[PDB]
Image: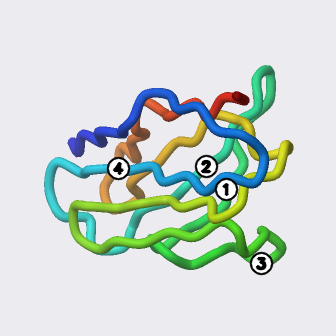
Amino acid sequence: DIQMTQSPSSLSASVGDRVTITCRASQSISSYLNWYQQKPGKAPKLLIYDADDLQSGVPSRFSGSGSGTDFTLTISSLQPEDFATYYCQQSYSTPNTFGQGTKVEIK
């Protein structure tokens, strides 16, 4: 089992702001780290995989960084469609496990 710790739990930002979210894995997962976005009532959608491989058709304002145990998701310039809960998920080991999520909330 691998435990994923996300920080912060929630944050406040306005449209246009840059936001950073962190994810720590309990042991190394090299670059097998995925970022998901979830809107309330809806399923999680994959934004980044392989730690920093932005999925085709996902906007460039989303970027991932990190390798090993420490990962970051940066949203460089928030659009209103970006307010959501973001999860990291390790895909190194089964069961794949999610962080607790960070809610990015409108200010």
* 40 sits to left or right of 31: right
Instruction: Please give the residue where the numbered disc 3 appears in the rendered image.
Output: 56
Q: Of label 3 and label 2, which has the lower sequence position?
A: 2
The C terminus lies in which quarter of the figure?
A: top right
User: In the rendered image, which residue does mark 2 sit on?
Assistant: 36
**Secondary structure beneath label 2:** strand
Tell me: residue 106, above or below residue 45.
Answer: above
Q: Residue at x 35, y 61 (%)?
A: 71
Looking at the image, which residue is at 43% across and 28% down? 9
Label 3 element class: loop
Question: Quick check: 62 above or below 103?
Answer: below
Residue contact at pointers 1 and 2, CB within 8 angstroms: yes
> Which amino acid lies under the numbered mark 4 shown in the image of this protein?
Cys
Q: Which amino acid, mark 2?
A: Tyr
* Nearest the eye: 107 or 22: 107
> Which residue in the protein does label 1 denote?
46
The mark that comes first in sequence, 1 or 4, is 4
- Residue 79, compared with residue 69, is above or below; it is above
Closer to the chain start, of discs 1 and 2, is: 2
Give, as a three-letter code, the residue at label 1.
Leu
Residue 104: image x %, image y %? 62, 35
Q: CA distance from mark 4 to mark 3?
A: 22 Å
Residue found farthest to the left: 27
Q: CA distance from mark 1 to mark 4?
A: 16 Å
